[PDB]
Amino acid sequence: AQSVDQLIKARGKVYFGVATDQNRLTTGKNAAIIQADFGMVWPENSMQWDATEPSQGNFNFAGADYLVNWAQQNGKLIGGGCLVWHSQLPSWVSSITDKNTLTNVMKNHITTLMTRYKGKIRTWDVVGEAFNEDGSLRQTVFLNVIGEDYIPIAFQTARAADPNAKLYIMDYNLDSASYPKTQAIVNRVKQWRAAGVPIDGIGSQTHLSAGQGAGVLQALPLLASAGTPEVSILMLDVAGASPTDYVNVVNACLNVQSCVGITVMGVADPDSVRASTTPLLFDGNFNPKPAYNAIVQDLQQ
Ligand SMILES: O=[N+]([O-])c1ccc2nn[nH]c2c1
Image 1 (cartoon, protein in one colour):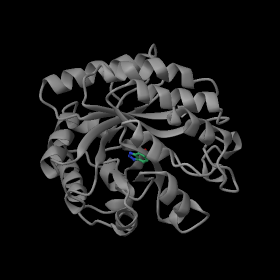
Image 2: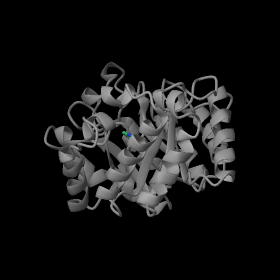
Image 3: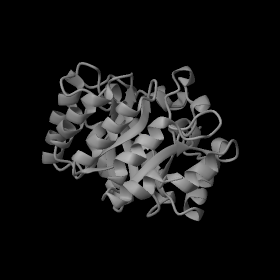
Image 4: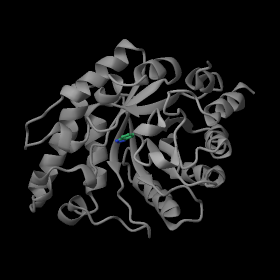
């Protein structure tokens, strides 16, 4: 049928993307759909810390290499991440108690991953899920051991490793303008950038319930008011996959000049972590759902 990536590019955006990995690319009809309809791929798991650095200084790149090679052969942009994210850490990192040791470990992790793929990765998610729901910083091993400087250090280290990449901070529950986490991340990113921290983007990890798409029309412009060169929608899925919810999210990005694109959490409903809510754009037979066709219609205008 029609490609949402082709159409969103024709409207002046950069991509419509999807998360995947080697497993998915060799099963189902995922590779054919990604080839035809999406312009950017992200590794769901193969670039996370537990997958890439299972013991200190010893890296495993097999799965990440597979994705990067596949993307290059198929003409797709690549996003990578997450470089610093508490929920994907191997136990050897979480057990470090010394500030200088953890700082060097974090810098080496960032530099090694980014150097390997230098010039090939459009966007890196550098820090993920750093905020509590009340807007304070989440008390992870990095905050407890290094302190709040871990965020500036991570971004500075990433900028030096690959100056071509766009560097993002990413979080979830940024879907409502009035929710405390949303204004908190805006305030902190503005302050960090004023201090010279190279944060190029805010990525909103958008997991919606039915009817919540409309709120993104106000939340996304508010995130853009932090002044980063880019914002994006990441990890998108919507319980019930209503066309209304999906079109509202797409229109939010179209309405925000600095929104470069949208990435969905996967291809087909049965492979979702909440499959019983049928929250994706393709069904269990790999056919496009009404929400896919509604996005196509919205973009053709
Ligand atoms: O947009 N994504 O689907 C996605 C998946 C995994 C990630 N890890 N870091 N950033 C990510 C984005």
